[PDB]
Structure formats: C-alpha cells, structure tokens
Length: 89
Picture 1 (cartoon, rainbow, N blue to C red):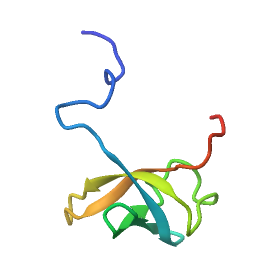
Picture 2: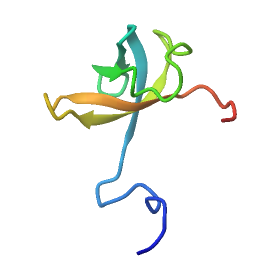
Picture 3: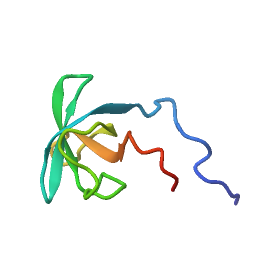
Picture 4: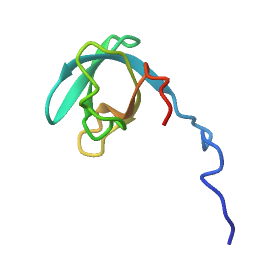
C-alpha cells in the first residue's frame, strides 16, 4: 500500500476544536473541568489527561477536546492537556 502518519490533522471536513476551562473538581478516579467558554461543568476522566494527574490540581487551566460518549452520548472531555507547561518533552 503506502506509508504515512494520519496525514496532517485536522482530518476530514469537520476539524477538531480544542476547548479550555478550569479544573472545578478532581478525584482519584477522575475530575471535572468548568468550561470558561460555554459556562458548563465538564467531566474529564483521569485517562484523558496525557500528563500525570499528580501534577494536575483543582483550580488550574487545562486544554481538552469536547466529544460525545457512546453510552450516554453526553459531552465529555478527552485527551486533556495542561495549558501552562512549556517544559520540553
């Protein structure tokens, strides 16, 4: 066939829009992020966050992507990523 790495997102007509808010609540299993754009409290799973929840905390800005679940179809956060942190990787 051919080679390549998912071309160069965004892919498909509909692109991916990342939203930013704040960590309203946080737990050992997951946490909630208060969207400062839609004024709604989102629910992000500890799995979404790429970094280490340890670093994360309640009251810190974070970037995520609003998606739709498959069990409830509700707007949940995914692939969370702390905004502040220009540190290399």
